[PDB]
Amino acid sequence: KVFGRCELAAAMKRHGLDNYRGYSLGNWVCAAKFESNFNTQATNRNTDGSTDYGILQINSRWWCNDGRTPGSRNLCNIPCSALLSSDITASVNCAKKIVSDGNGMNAWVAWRNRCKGTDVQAWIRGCRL
Ligand code: NA
Image (cartoon, rainbow, N blue to C red):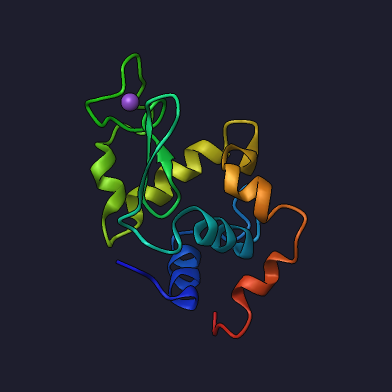
């Protein structure tokens, strides 16, 4: 599924991401824009041989099992394919584990490089929330 911007903001808020571990909702929408272009089906190979999956591009080295990443953990206890659903529940629950770890949202390379330090609020402008 390719979400609209305000559609995804509403779904992330419903699932409890607004101000989760101190990160406002625009941060989570901006990360999704630059990680996946709002597309649940997005998949991208990493140079280390792992792969990133779904709306928030969650990695197979530590977080999910995709069957093809040697020496890897599955800390969210899920098949990586679960992260491609039109239902974002799996992506959200895994993200809540990642963001609690200690590095916060710096775990997402696109957030650090394109969202951090910008007017992220702009990503929810016009939305009835
Ligand atoms: Na894995």
